[PDB]
Image (cartoon, coloured by chain):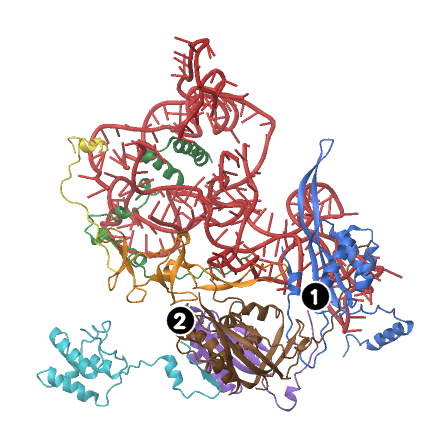
Amino acid sequence: HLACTAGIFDPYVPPEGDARMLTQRTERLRKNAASQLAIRKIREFDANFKTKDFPEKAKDIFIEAHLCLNNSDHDRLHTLVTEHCFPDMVWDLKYKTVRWGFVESLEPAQVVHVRCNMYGQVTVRLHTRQTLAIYDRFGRLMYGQEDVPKDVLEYVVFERHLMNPYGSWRMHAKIVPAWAPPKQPILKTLMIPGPQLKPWEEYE
Amino acid sequence: ISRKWEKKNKIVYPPQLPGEPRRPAEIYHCRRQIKYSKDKMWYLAKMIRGMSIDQALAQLEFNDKKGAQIIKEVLLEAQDMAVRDHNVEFRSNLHIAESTSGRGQCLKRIRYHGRGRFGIMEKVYCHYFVKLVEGPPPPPEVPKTAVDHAKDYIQQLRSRTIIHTL
Amino acid sequence: FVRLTLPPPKVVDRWNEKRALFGVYDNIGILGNFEKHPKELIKGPVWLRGWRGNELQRCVRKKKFVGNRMFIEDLHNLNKRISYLYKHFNRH
Amino acid sequence: YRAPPPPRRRPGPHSPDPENLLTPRWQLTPRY
Amino acid sequence: VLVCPPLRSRAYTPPSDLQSRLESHIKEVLGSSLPNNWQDISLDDGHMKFRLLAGLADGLGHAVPNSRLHQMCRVRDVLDFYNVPVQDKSKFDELVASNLPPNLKISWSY
Amino acid sequence: TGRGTSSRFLTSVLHNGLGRYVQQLQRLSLSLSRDAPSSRGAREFVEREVTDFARRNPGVVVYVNPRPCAMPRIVAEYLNGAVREENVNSKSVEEIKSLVQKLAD
Amino acid sequence: HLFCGDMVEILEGKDAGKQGKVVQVVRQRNWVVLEGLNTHYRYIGRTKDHRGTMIASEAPLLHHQVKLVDPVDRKPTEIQWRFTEAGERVRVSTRSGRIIPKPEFPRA
RNA sequence: AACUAAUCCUAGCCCUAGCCCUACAAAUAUAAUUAUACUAUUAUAUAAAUCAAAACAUUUAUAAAAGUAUUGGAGAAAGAAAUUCGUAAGGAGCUAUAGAACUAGUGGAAAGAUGAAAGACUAAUUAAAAGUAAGAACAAGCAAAGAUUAAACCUUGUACCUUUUGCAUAAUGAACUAACUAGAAAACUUCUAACUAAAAGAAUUACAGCUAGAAACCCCGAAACCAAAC
């Protein structure tokens, strides 16, 4: 049984400068021609799905899922996110302790684009300041700052199984806009090994 | 069979506080099944105790015993995971804190003899245990000088207490 | 060496029908006008109902009671066991 | 619980079946 | 359709007007209305004993024990038997209401 | 045994008797079971002698906690922090009283 | 009384109280499998190169952990086996007696 | 926190009760299992001895009356009838060195252990035996004891079991760890009670007896002897 499908039905293209940006909401009003028919399909199974109010529900799941990481609440996070999302979140956090906190959101979350036997994926736009600090098995700090807020803008895709009676909205994937700044680098320094050659061969 | 050496590598310490020195890394690696005598392997372990990672590797490369080659392979595996999984920045910054060998489960057979005699044949197996601490090997011990020896003797004389008296 | 695991918890009911009704009619003879002797209420091997004896006596009585219904193998074994028992008690 | 009915010996004459092999001979004699 | 009445305590204290209830019981139970030397009257009569003891038990609230039943030959025994107090208070209950000192702590975990 | 056992020198806690004597024992705890033959002797002790000891020594905290218990136990705590436990299983009133007096001293 | 395709309510388990359709029945262990219910998440394709892909895998449910559902009223009604006019055995609810027709299951 | 190891409960059994029983093809007694001719085709005398009689010889068991009488190297022991009387699934058993030898007749063994789910990455749990490692040793001595500020020094002290004389500087036996491994019967007495010139739920004893209860006597090991097979 699969309650989620990897990938996005149609990839929404974020416009550069959207962080600076009513306005964008009207752009959705202009673009509901592409998306309203999709919105109707979610509405048909639910009838209470509105692009205006979904971000509030979507935001809680996103924040709640991040909180589970600190407590390693795998069972709780399992419900919040889809099967595809869960392994990525926690696989690289094995044998690590992370302190994550959510600072006030810079801008309100808004639905951006939705698509849809039937799996509905809703893109949500979120800019929020957060604090991240990850330590080693020995407790040594390896990445992030304990109490430094980092402002990050990303687009988060939630998914639900419309056909299933118990289907619910669970975080599936995140769309990263190209104009977003690169993530902070690791504290430690890495070494790139040189080319490997056989005894007969010579360096090139 | 007990495999508590591996569990020592699965230990996760609590997050270190700001007012705490950076914890040195400790790695526990072992090979459970080796077709070699523990007693013979122990000699190799004893010599390498306390030496640096590079110094031990160099000696192993020029060692004639079969166990030494196995030890070098075991050492290389531990070093690789240490950087890959134990967040070791420098490959050279490793030294042999502990090295020892243990008995392993053997196989039993009957040893025939050409003159009608028989014997108990045993196929020996052993375990090899090593713990590696990140950092250079500790400085070697310095023999006590005559001044140090005399001071202790005088201190002992002063420390003497009267026995069995009011 | 000793167990490293706990045994299953056990609770015993002392007022079950078997225990509750245990001993009833033990006074059948005195309270029943002696029409039925309490020995008549003994349940067990036929050759020792209402009768007691030493191990040799019990085996001998068993042989007589069910000798016609005993297996040849059992009968042969009983005879051999009886012979050893007879010598020990009657000579040592 | 309620105690079971008291055991009772069957009264009255009882005639063994002569044809039955199991019935002991002494129970079929005129003295019987 | 049968409902149990509330359980009744076995604690009995001699009434202040003990004789009043006693004599009234005899005055009613006994036709002679408490005759001379009532204390020394015998209770061997079955009918009189049942009426007197039952009436006293209901009115007073204390009943003669079956083990002590035969001892009630004379009214003197009945009068003496009733006048002795009976308390249901447990030993722990008595200890609780015994001016517990500050350094002594009691807690009933049952 | 002396070689295999520890020893100490004569000493006093803090010169207790120089100015005024202070009782080291600070707390006594008694556990009892309402229905247990082992506690019968302890059961009677509470009725008769527990009060007298409390009056004689009012500076010791006394705890009496009847509870379902397999074996009654007495716990004595001292000012210095020493704690000693004595089982009262199937012990008479006289035995209990003697032990308490020794503990106080 | 449980057959593949039967709508049943999970008396106890991870998804207790969620009605599902049977898809596999291991009668030897009295196990009933409901698709999309009592479904845990596990890694498929775990290999040296890749960690693996999370998938939802159903877990067995014992027979006592499920009960049949009356079509008109969705409840875990106890059923009793009785024949029909055609002679085919049909489970009948002990209370609110009704015929639960045998479900249609696609060929494996 | 280590190694070697250890950990577990059902694999199953035992005794009574109940119950008698009447549970593919192809090839085969030739050379059994060789699809058709050979070549006729066929068990079994008292059971004895061993054993007991401390050897050995006649001899030696295999409901009440009653262990009375007789018999018997009168000894180890053997022992009627008359005459009365006679309807009718469980375990103060065992649980992988225990219980059947057994998971198995594979003369005759050895052994297995996660969880509800492995279509949840196969489980944990234990300073736990001896043996080792972590951590070689430091004048002096049955290895400890009294001690001591102090591990060793100073002081005191002729390993153990059994057996010899109530003595070993004799002599036997012991590499060590775990499990297994040797006293069993009531005729009479004392004691505990019931009832009493009577006692006992039939068969017994009685001039205080009679009835019930309680109280007891090992293990391993020959050279041998005989029967029946091979």
Which chain did the renderer colour brown? A
Instruction: Look at chain D in the picture and name its colour.
Output: yellow
Give the chain letter at badge 1.
B
Residue A103 vs residue C23, the one in the foreground: A103
Q: Secondary structure at mark 2?
A: loop
- Which residue lies at the image location 28% right of the left edge and 83% below the top edge? E85
x and y percentages locating residue G98 in the rendered image? 25, 61
Instruction: Look at chain F in the picture and name its colour.
Output: purple
Residue H186 vs residue E62, the one in the foreground: E62
Instruction: Look at chain G in the picture and name its colour.
Output: orange
Residue H148 vs residue H56: left or right? right
The disc placed on residue F35 is 2
x and y percentages locating residue D25 in the rendered image? 21, 30
Q: Quadrant of residue C47?
A: top left
- Which residue lies at the image location 21% right of the left edge and 90% below the top edge? E17
Q: Which residue is mark 1?
A: B84
Instruction: Look at chain C in the picture and name its colour.
Output: green
Q: Quadrant of residue H145?
A: bottom right
Residue A169 vs residue E36: left or right? right
Residue C89 vs residue B101: left or right? left
Give the chain letter at badge 2.
F
- Which residue lies at the image location 70% right of the left edge and 61% below the top edge? B29
Which amino acid is tagged 1? Answer: Arg
Callout 2 crowding tier (Cα within 10 Å): few <14, some 14–19, many ≥20: few
Which chain did the renderer colour red? H
Instruction: Look at chain B in the picture and name its colour.
Output: blue
